[PDB]
Image 1 (tube, rainbow, N blue to C red):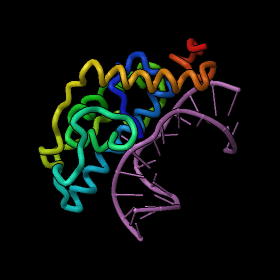
Image 2 (cartoon, protein in one colour):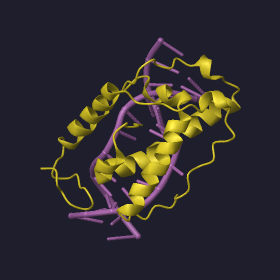
Image 3 (cartoon, protein in one colour):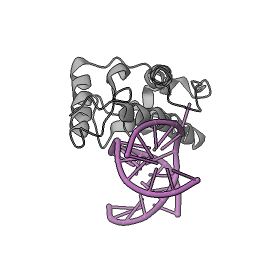
Length: 137
DNA sequence: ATCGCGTTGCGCT
DNA sequence: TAGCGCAACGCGA
């Protein structure tokens, strides 16, 4: 799974879709632990953004950032006209507030997010499209 | 109607 | 501890 701090407006159509269906994977992971009775401090949450091991856990006390991000993601998808079935931002009022914090990415964390996108496109530049067209490559 | 491709970490056994 | 498969799907060829 992967969450980017990248502005959704410049996301490659593919990276935009992958994020649409991937982001919601965190709300569910948290709900499940909450079901298991786990608390936010029973998790090794990173002090700073990271990609890889510790990545999604990082977002375990930033459910707002994502919730809000979900609204942004949904918008862009519609703009480009992708027939998405879930046009509704999910209701996370059922989760202990300790998990629902906002998060203000630092300029350095974002650049890191970009780097990944920018090296994942390069693996297949002709294949990545923006609003239907292969602007990369 | 079908097939490849997009992420990759983390929860559970 | 180690390994395994899960977890918001829809588009272009």
